[PDB]
Image 1 (cartoon, rainbow, N blue to C red):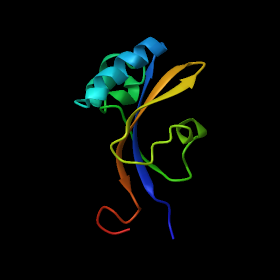
Image 2: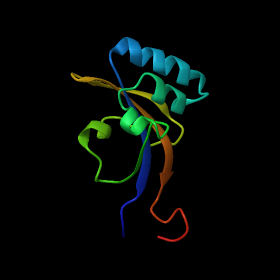
Image 3: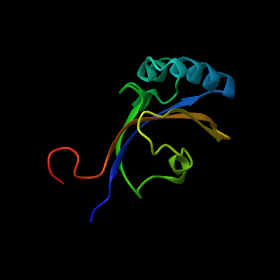
Length: 102
């Protein structure tokens, strides 16, 4: 009995306009990573292709709890914040064991 892990990619946009520009491109579904590096103020982490890294389930901050991204491949999650708009993408889903042996 251990926590499953989720790989989220997230990028911060200046306005909803920026978010729409980002989600419009990823709506075609070609590259999210590209969108991440160019406009996002996330780029401290976005330079990794928008990948924030593998987080463990139930260690997730409430911000991404509202992202609703449990199904792998689902992108264009726009999180409305006062600080700006966050774009969340699902890179992968692992039920803990999924790698070699957990």
